Length: 235
Length: 234
Ligand SMILES: Nc1ncnc2c1ncn2[C@@H]1O[C@H](COP(=O)(O)OC(=O)CCCC[C@@H]2SC[C@@H]3NC(=O)N[C@@H]32)[C@@H](O)[C@H]1O
Ligand SMILES: Nc1ncnc2c1ncn2[C@@H]1O[C@H](COP(=O)(O)OC(=O)CCCC[C@@H]2SC[C@@H]3NC(=O)N[C@@H]32)[C@@H](O)[C@H]1O
Image (cartoon, rainbow over the protein chains, first blue to last red):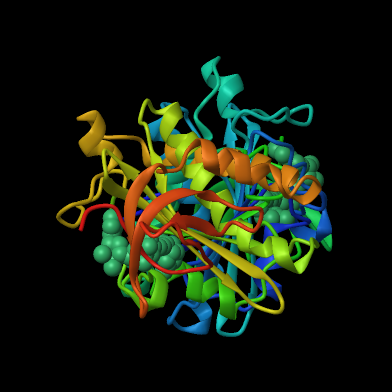
């Protein structure tokens, strides 16, 4: 009854009034590529390192099952597909979303969405949490808070799915194309702190041909950051 | 993201851009009670006796998984829940649907919807097909044809699911209530032709406590139909 016209993402959609986590359900269940798992609310939503992700009613909490036929070295770019898709949807609604490497989308430096990719061989789960009409943690923001009015949740869903399908199809043909889109929508030219085994500060200059964040430390030393066990903090 | 407020029916909804049949999927897949299976289009839609149910884009083709812990003899009333739900939804959109025993809904005698209930040991599948904006077979009709304008398919889905959830919850407590709602919205007091071997004609008088169609033949004989097809124009 939804009338989706996408090629892969959205071929099937499983909706839940409530769920523990769409990412956990997607990883665990036997599902076809392109299947979207969406819930009004999550009781155990999570971010990276099982950090908690608040998922109250009013937001868009979903996961997409993918089985990308691309070299193993390109799978780390899947997170960017989600981030860019969210940015394009926000722009369609006249909201200036910007990417905080490598998985977050901010509006005026306030978190409005997050992307979590979990992979297991031939199966990749692309999870996306976007604040629309829901209440949010202090510091975060939402489409409703940004626009000053409630936003039809289903319209945002249709927008995002349409964007993701297109981005995904192009990624399968040209895995590198997504990097240019990230670059054009990412927060760069500012000082950031990288937190992992220890930490260092520098200017976030750009992302390289592998999607690694390039940081120039005050000494002039250049570091290439691989996302995985590190987080980014703005100064 | 649909924000359904129903208690049982619609707790989960599985949507397909295309499928063979929502009833078939529902029967062969383990699904919690209340799960709704819906598709934009079916390539092998089914009617009774495996008749074909045209299910092109624009209509509402769905199946609901049920597991009612009620007496065995009340299970034949599930089809009525689907029929009455459709009638209620049609009324909300200013359309007067009438039930043609035991599973069809007609508007001015043209078929607009059909119900197919299939029992399984593990569950009961309530299948409902309703013409909204799609092209229909000659002799049939749709909400769009009746209203003269495109009808928001999702609005119809929300309405129907809401009505069914309410009807089902009450059915679990007062299983006989559905019968009167059926009598109130069924085509009666007219001559009909019951089909199958031993075909016969007579006045469709009412339905009994088991949902059987009561027919009065011209001889005065009274027959009770458990299942079969009724023709209002022959
Ligand atoms: N609703 C919210 N809006 C903005 N920030 C939030 C938030 N909830 C939590 N946060 C903050 O974001 C931090 C984590 O951000 P990270 O970058 O580590 O982790 C993420 O940003 C990824 C979040 C992915 C959530 C989606 S919802 C659908 C799918 N199912 C899931 O269970 N997860 C995915 C938390 O520690 C909080 O500081
Ligand atoms: N789309 C349509 N609209 C009005 N009449 C139709 C129609 N398609 C077929 N018909 C006519 O109705 C007859 C069958 O009516 P019956 O009363 O026997 O059988 C029915 O009326 C029940 C139809 C149930 C269809 C739903 S769609 C979702 C679920 N999954 C399925 O595969 N099926 C269910 C066909 O033989 C045609 O004569």
